[PDB]
Every structure is written in structure tokens, then in C-alpha cells.
Amino acid sequence: SVEVEILLNDAESRKRAEHKTEDGKKEKYFLFYDGETVSGKVSLSLKNPNKRLEHQGIKIEFIGQIELYYDRGNHHEFVSLVKDLARPGEITQSQAFDFEFTHVEKPYESYTGQNVKLRYFLRATISRRLNDVVKEMDIVVHTLSTYPSSIKMEVGIEDCLHIEFEYNKSKYHLKDVIVGKIYFLSVEIKIKHMEIDIIKRETTGTGPNVYHENDTIAKYEIMDGAPVRGESIPIRLFLAGYELTPTMRDINKKFSVRYYLNLVLIDEEERRYFKQQEVVLWRKGD
């Protein structure tokens, strides 16, 4: 009947970006940053030039919302901009309408999680008697940060089985390298297994309930049973190869995405020793 398209000014001139959708598959989208104007036009195409189209209005909305999978259809919009493009009337021809949203606040980076999604999109609606024609196009938003030592954590018991992991920063950009050292402070008991993990923890608030999802992004296993006091081991973790998002902290009080270095030690007696410490991941502007 009618084919609605959303078309941005400078479509093929503006940056795209890859973003994973709910299935886990990648795809590209127009990339925007906080503030940036969002402008283009809504293009209507009449299926048969020989036929009128009665509507109760045509509008374009810019929306940023958080969708909680445990309350799925109940969207939480945090930015909503509405521009009416036509009064209730009749379409008797193919045509387009211009729109411009200036000063578009986008305080949060796009995110597609396990129990939650944060997305921005344009929505064109042709209001109708029975059912509206709705067309959405997603855009992706990134947030850039900038930042300027050494950090230590330890696992185990003093003077028994005791390890120390030291690394260079408490914050890393998404293509950074985590550079550190395992120091064997004391190897009284034999080491059955050791590893350093990067763990992503997704915390989702929905109603009176909190949901928790952990994803082990990387595990660097330490080799052999050769350790003796004073011996150390170098660690270099390249973040770039991994799928990583910036840290997201209490986004509109609905969810957090946090990253942790997690030190795992299993002794010859099958005993687990865990320690973890947060690293803040941030996105660096090219």
C-alpha cells in the first residue's frame, strides 16, 4: 500500500558502526554521538499511483529507550522527540517530508545484553483508521572518554599457597593491552591450576528484582607445575581481539555492565581460591 523509508542527510557520508543484535549476530548502523543533530526525510512510496491513502497524521520520532527482557514489552524511554510532519489528510502521490532534530541528547552508549537492551531509533508513523504504518530504523550511539601507576591483587593464604597478580592500570580502552605479572609469593602447597579471567558482569534491575549474568570474555591459563617462591610470570592480555563494550554503570538505574580481572587458583588438594577486581573499560575517540 505505502512503503515508508527513513533517509538521513549525508547518508553515505556519515560514519557507520558494527553492532550485535539480539540473536548474537553483527550488522552495521549509522553512528551518532551525544548532541549531534539528527536530520533527514521520511519518504513515502505509493504502491499504486492509482490509489489514495487516508491517514490521521504522519510523524517522525527520535527515541532512546531501555528494554528489560524480564518485563519485555514495557519500554523505558529516556529520550523522546516528536515532530509531526503532516495533519490528518490524504496522500495522493509519492512524496517525502524533511525533519531535523537538533541538540539530540544521547547520554548512553547502545547496548545489546542478555537481560536488557539499550537502543536508539527513528520511528516514522502513518496514523490510520485501523492499523498504522510504522517504520523504524535503529541508529547506534557510542560514548567517548579520555584518561591520563600499578595495581595489585592477591589470592591465597600467607606463607602457605599465595599468589599476587600485578597489572598496569585500573582503566583500559577497548583496544588496550593489560600488562602484568604473576608473583609466586609462597608455594608451600602444589599448584594444580591457575588462570586470569576477564569477566563481564551484567546486572539488570527490573521491578523489585535484580538479574545477573556473567560472561567469561577471556581466560589466560598459567602453564605447568614448575612454580617456586620468587618466580614470576609475565602477562599480556590484548583487549582488541575480544568483543568488548565500555563499562556501563547504573544506566538510568536500570542496569550495569562491569568488567573484572578474576584470579583463579586451584591447589593440589582441589581447593579453589578466587579474587577479582574491577577494571573500567572505556571507548577512545579515533
Image: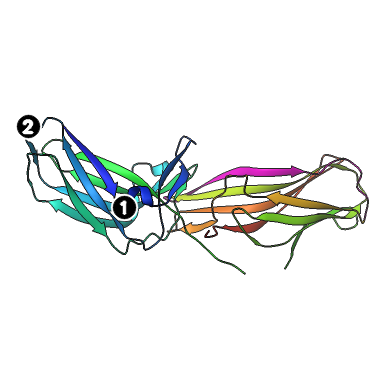
First to last magenta residue range: 207-229
Helix, strand or loop for disc 2: loop
Q: From the image, state whether disc 1 or disc 2 is nearer to you.
A: 2
Tag on residue 51? 2
Dividing the image into 4 quarters, which one contains the N terminus? top left
Residue 6 relative to residue 241: left or right: left
Q: Residues within 10 Å of mark 1 (few under 14, many from 20)?
A: many
In the displayed structure, would residue 115 be above or below residue 169?
Answer: above
Alpha carbons under labels 1 and 2: distance apart: 32 Å
Amino acid type indicated by mark 1: Ile
Q: Residue at x 46, y 44 (%)?
A: 19
Amino acid type indicated by mark 2: Lys
Q: Residue at x 85, y 54 (%)?
A: 162
Residue 46 relative to residue 185: left or right: left
Q: Quadrant of residue 283?
A: bottom right
Colour treatment of the image: rainbow
Label 1 or label 2, whichever comes before in sequence order: 2
In the displayed structure, would residue 93 be above or below residue 57?
Answer: above
Tag on residue 93? none
Q: Residues within 10 Å of mark 2 (few under 14, many from 20)?
A: few
Location of residue 204 in the rendering, given as x and y in whole percent from the top left corner: 48, 49
Tag on residue 63? 1
Location of residue 14 in the rendering, given as x and y in whole percent from the top left corner: 38, 52
